[PDB]
Amino acid sequence: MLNPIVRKFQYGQHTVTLETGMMARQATAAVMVSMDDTAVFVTVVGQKKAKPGQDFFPLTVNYQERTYAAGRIPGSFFRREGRPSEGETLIARLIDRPIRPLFPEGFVNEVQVIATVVSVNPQVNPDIVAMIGASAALSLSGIPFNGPIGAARVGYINDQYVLNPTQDELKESKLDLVVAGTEAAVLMVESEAQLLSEDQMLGAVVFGHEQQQVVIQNINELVKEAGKPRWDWQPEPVNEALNARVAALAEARLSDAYRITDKQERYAQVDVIKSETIATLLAEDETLDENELGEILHAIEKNVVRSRVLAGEPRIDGREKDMIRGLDVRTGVLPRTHGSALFTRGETQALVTATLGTARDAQVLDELMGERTDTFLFHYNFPPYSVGETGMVGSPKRREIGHGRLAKRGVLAVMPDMDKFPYTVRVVSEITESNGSSSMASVCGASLALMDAGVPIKAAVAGIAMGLVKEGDNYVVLSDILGDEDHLGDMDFKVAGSRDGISALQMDIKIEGITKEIMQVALNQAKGARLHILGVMEQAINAP
Amino acid sequence: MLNPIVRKFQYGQHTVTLETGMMARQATAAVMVSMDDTAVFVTVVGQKKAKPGQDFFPLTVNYQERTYAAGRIPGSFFRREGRPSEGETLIARLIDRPIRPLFPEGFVNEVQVIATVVSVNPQVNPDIVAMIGASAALSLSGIPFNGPIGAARVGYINDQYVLNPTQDELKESKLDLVVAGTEAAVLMVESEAQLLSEDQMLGAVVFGHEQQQVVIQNINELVKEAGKPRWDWQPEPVNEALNARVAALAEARLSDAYRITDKQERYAQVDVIKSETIATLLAEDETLDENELGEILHAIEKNVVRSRVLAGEPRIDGREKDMIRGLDVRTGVLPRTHGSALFTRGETQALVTATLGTARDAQVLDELMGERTDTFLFHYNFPPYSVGETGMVGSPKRREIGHGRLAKRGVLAVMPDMDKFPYTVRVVSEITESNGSSSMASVCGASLALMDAGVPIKAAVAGIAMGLVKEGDNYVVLSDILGDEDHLGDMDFKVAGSRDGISALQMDIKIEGITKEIMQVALNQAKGARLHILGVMEQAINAP
Amino acid sequence: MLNPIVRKFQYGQHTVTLETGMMARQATAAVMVSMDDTAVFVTVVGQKKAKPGQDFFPLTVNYQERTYAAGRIPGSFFRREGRPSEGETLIARLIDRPIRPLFPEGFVNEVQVIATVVSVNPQVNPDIVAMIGASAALSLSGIPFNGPIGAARVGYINDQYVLNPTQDELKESKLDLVVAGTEAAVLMVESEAQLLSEDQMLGAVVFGHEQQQVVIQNINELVKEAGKPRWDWQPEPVNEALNARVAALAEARLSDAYRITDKQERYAQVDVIKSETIATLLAEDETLDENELGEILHAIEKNVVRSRVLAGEPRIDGREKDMIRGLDVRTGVLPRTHGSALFTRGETQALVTATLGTARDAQVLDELMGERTDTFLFHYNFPPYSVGETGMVGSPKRREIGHGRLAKRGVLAVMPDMDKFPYTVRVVSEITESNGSSSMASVCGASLALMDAGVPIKAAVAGIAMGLVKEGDNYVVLSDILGDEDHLGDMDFKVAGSRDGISALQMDIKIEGITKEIMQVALNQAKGARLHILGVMEQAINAP
């Protein structure tokens, strides 16, 4: 006989139960989460010795909702679920994003987080239930993983924050955000609100982070109770011999390379510097490990950008911190469509179109919690010609779907109700070129496309992404980040809203140690830039 | 003018016609086997040149069912037969399973045996017609094949046997099995029975094997008449200079490596030896093939386990040759689903669920013969976290479909009729951990899920797997085999049924020379092992 | 801030507008094309450096129609276009085919042509608009391209040729062809014509070629205005010391290798020479490249065949310049289906079947501009066993859909109306062996299958493909070419029709400098071979 080890704790209005060490033993980690009646079984499998020819951390999270959870036989032709829907893909991204940055730098081992829904209650979502599982299992696995993260859902009724609102409570609620992060700092946040202000939008993030602290403490006690011992992993020793040998040839040229304004001219230049430096090092001796060099050159690229921002020197394209790129607004680009828009910011632009139809063309979503019909439709396409390369095209990938739901949340608060406008609207965003924010601009393109179409929107809506360069305690907040300022930066602080308030913001932080004090600066500077986008948008069109 | 080579012979109540030499002359083999209204054109293509590193034998069988065989336009959006359905995959396995062990060891050349149905009779099933088709083609191809095999459906009407029962006669029949084997011995068997005794179930396998002998004789005469010259292929010359060089270094390590008992600790130890023995030989001589060294180590692994079980000595986990693994019967493990079950046998586990629905949720099967509705549903999911590896959560592999119907056949005889219980039942089996037989454990969890849901089944149903190790003429029968035992053994003898009779039986023999005398011993020992599972199941629940 | 470069002109009636320099700046080239209201946004991306291990030229043209162009929400389940349809792949091939031979010999850099429909007029067809867009983008990119090409649709109303007919004007027309080619010579060509004569079909190609000249002139002027400078590219230099080194060892017996008749004996002989020549050259020195030696051997294979045909020597299988291979006509090959046919030409055969149905079984094509329901279906299947190789079977390949419609082009014109025959007919072609033209042999098998089914077709239809060997100004026209005479040849000239007129005409030229006189001779010589097949076809069956 095998007996499981359990621990029960009160969380909000529901009693969350965690179980381990009875179901999957062959898997490195296995926990079964049960908020109140909704259960999600999460397993984490990680290899001890991965491949040697790996340069990227290969983490994959597969979220899947079982049909027997609600107690219904699937409506598919084969009577068996198959491909994940738009709902299941968004939750998969909601679990990956917070857990990714907690892994130590230099960890290249393949890990897979399989989260399957067991049972479901029509009141409690299982999003946040699955996020606790990936937080509990990964801490019990032994795999080097900081945290663990807490999962919290924030509501807003009567100008006051409510922890974990049900489906019936969400009908009267104004704000709907999911907050995740470690005990020390916040890590992500996915929001969907009405038109709240800047102060109350930040207060909900702090509220949820304080409430999720109960979950974090209960997992930590379970690690010392049933958790497997930590992996004996050590990062590759910092070779000071090569870090001065490569830098004496590359750091001098790469410092001058990051002053070019054009993206095409800069990326072609840094590729040449990376090519001939390795070519010379291979000509010296064939012992030097190729990849190794690729990470040293990448470390120099990170050091050149970050140090110049902290000192007070001009950015890549030679732009101050609170300064943004130039704007180009074009309404009515297509001839035989309902609505069309061409919004351009610097060197990134989105061809956004709007379509109108009857209520019969509504998307009938067969969700696990309940069957609902979606009136407003938003689609995000990211073709390879935007970044300037070749790739596969046909079916939308993870992001494509994630950024599409993001741009939907930023407009959903503005969109008129069915009582005034009873027509199904489909908005398609086509990324023509991409350098900084592609999900954001869109929201700017959607507002121009919906007016042009004839949709009576409440107020013009815009949005821009923010960044951060943090080293020690001091920090610099960036307005309208570039491609090199996001991949080498510390966070992708996306904010979208109207003239009055904020519709929806996405918080993606890569480092731990983020504070509420530096959150206010990033929130306030985004509002000043948001009004600047709208000042040019209202210059072209101001009425539907 | 083109000319065909025709052979006709009487087989039961049907006449079988074999044509070769005119259709698909470019392919190594092409045989047109069409009985009384219906046929399955089968072609074999084998590459003369083997891969560069190819180690395993790549055999791929694609069985597809054209809709114009019955004379009907397919009911789809594209109006064309696309990817194979649940049915098409099953027959493909009935073609792939008997032919695979007949290919000689050391043969790594890629071969493809595809079968396409070109016309069809509502009374004669295309499954055995395709099996004879592949048997005739592979023998006429020239590719090293130790066949040919015969195909026969046995059935059971009025305490008697009838060779290849028709679709109308199958409704009155209490048995439905397809037997495949050579002139010397049996090789496979896929069966479905309505609670039959061991003597009647064993006598059915012998009956079908004796009746299919005329098929083998008629194929052999065609090979002597219109057969392509056999391939000049010889296995790698076995040298004792390299074998004893590894055996004096690895056999001592591998002997203690199979005494570890625990799966995770055994596989970790057995991988270390493989990773070190090859590495130490490469340090001494780097001109040796790594691919050859792994095949020798696999032969040593085969010699250690088989010799220990051949003599009176406990196996890899400490069990005797009839002793079965420990049991953990659990039900009502999940809250918000109709039926819950948790079955664990030693180191294998299956989370089985039950779901109830109306006649609206019935599976509408669009088969080649005609449209029918399926009331009982069974799905088999095999995730990567079961064995402790990383894979694509995606699905569903073939083995997943083949084992899905396997467990469906074991419960179908137990399941109540439509009149007494007019509800469509959906059963989903989730493999939590895998070691030994997980398909037989799915049948044990199925009965527990149905009783928890409230489904009034006839009796309790259970299932176990049996193994064999034979060297010369003497044999040792194993009860409830482990994973490896299945790979390093000789046969996968699966038996599923109740206390009274057998509901399902699968016979997957990988070696020829199997005796009728040893089959009645393995089936009788399986009955005693099945009653042990059923006794513990009745302890937790004996009625719904 | 952002300025476009625009040039608009006239092309018969609808004014064609071309725009570049604003949309998609990151990519290599992006041109906004359109006529009246139909707009197709085409992008071309070319990679600077080639992949180390490349031997072939990777051209991947993908055409995607988006439903917001017409102003309609898609009728799909997810409400997203996604994967390319049956129609979308045909236009993708219609763009890929003419542009492929224009790339210089030796160029191996990966290029992608992404053409997407963004706006559409219900009268103007996007297919010719997308072809102009790709022609403009490839010329403005700088990537080595020997264009530009023009696109013209030719109709035939009241014995007169009409340039670019609208969808309403096509109902009166008896011809619908899409002609493509450079300023000096024609390239590809696909037609469909209710039994028209040779001079009518030939004159229509010349008509469209002369009318599309104004398009090419306006593209060339735009390149002179705002075109990115031509790529600094130079092909691999001719190795005089290596080309003679291989020839003095391989060319001697490779000349005798293309002398034997049988395909299986020839392809085994040309492979065994290559397997021995390269093995000896690698043993002599290991500094040589694997792919470089194969390119010289292929040049020998090309030179041996072409030199014999041009001089006046007998062909590979011992045929004359106008001689057609042996024919085998069989019908009623299958028992339990409506239509059955087994047509064989030389060593190529197609198992063609005809299936009868009702109006309920008709395919509803959700095309961009249109709601038409197709009553006639044609499906082409090219399995791996036809060529004697091993591959993967699943979703119909681009080559299968292209030949499927191409075989449909010849049958649709001769088929009876819905008023006299109100049954939906499905035709499925199965290629069992292939060497010459299996797509045109499917048309011959289609007429035999329909007569066996009972379809009252107006006349019998047959056809063959034509080849040409031209290196100077003198030419040799070949009737019914092989696989070796098509790859090493210069053009693929497909003709299909009845005893009175031509139903289908396809033109696939790989070389520049095609004259008017060689196009009519290849068409007139095809008529003689077409009458030969129909004469043998009438011997078996003449009336249903």
Image (cartoon, coloured by chain):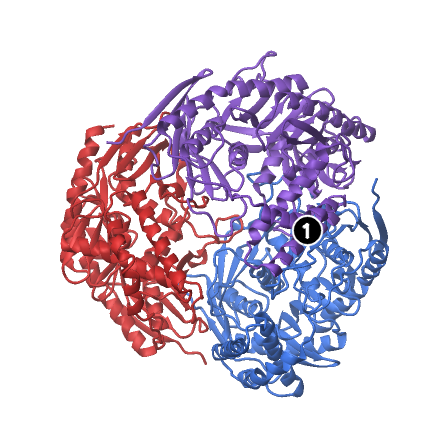
Chain colours: A blue, B purple, C red
Residue at left offset 57%, top offset 71%: A290
Residue B184 in view = yes
Classify residue A153 by image quadrant.
bottom right
Return the residue nearer the eye: A437 or C202: C202
Q: Is residue B155 above or below residue B139?
A: above
C66 left or right of B418?
Answer: left
In this orientation, which residue lies closer to the viewer: A338 or C513?
Answer: C513
Q: Is residue C188 visible?
A: no
Q: Is residue A385 left or right of residue C380?
A: right
Q: List the residue tagged with mark 1.
A: B249
Q: Mark 1: give few (<14), some (14-19) or many (20+) Cα within 10 Å.
A: few
Could you tell me which residue is drawn at 45 percent across and 54 percent down?
C72
Please, what is the three-letter code of the amino acid marked with disc 1?
Leu
Q: Quadrant of the N terminus of chain B?
A: top left
**Horizontal and vertical percent position of residue A110:** 65, 59
Which of the two residues, C177 or C111, is positioned nearer the viewer here?
A: C111
Question: Which chain's residue wears label 1?
Answer: B
Residue B334 at x, y percent in the picture: 76, 41
Q: Quadrant of residue A181?
A: bottom right
